[PDB]
Length: 84
RNA sequence: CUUAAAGAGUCAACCCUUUGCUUAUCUUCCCUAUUUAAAUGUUAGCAGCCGCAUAGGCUG
Image (cartoon, rainbow, N blue to C red; front, side, top):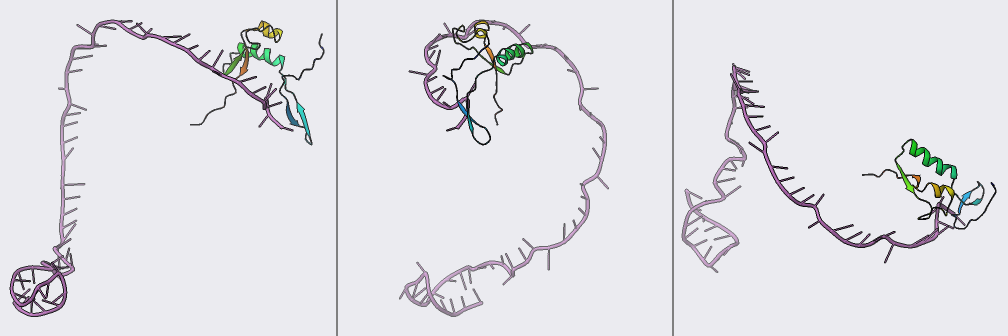
């Protein structure tokens, strides 16, 4: 079941240095991080955070986690302090 | 060589109705203000006639 698939379409593509050259790099999301972050920051009540529902109004499209956890995946609120 | 690359959130709203804050009272008792000197810079730069002069002189 666990194999590979490659579609850089719609996928951010950034350069990152290899030390003496560059390496064009595609950042994709982590599945363990998303579901584990939702469960843990809900069960230890972390509230300086966001909520994002992946898929839109039909969350059966993206993944199976999307389809089940339709309440919304939780993202960290990475807002810095503001002066004055 | 930036999760780079890119995108209209628009829309509408009756908050509102009523009310008892009341009552009460010892601020009082005492006090060393004190002492001492130059109005000076000279002081007031004035009162009038001699003249066209608000130019220049005289008079005390």
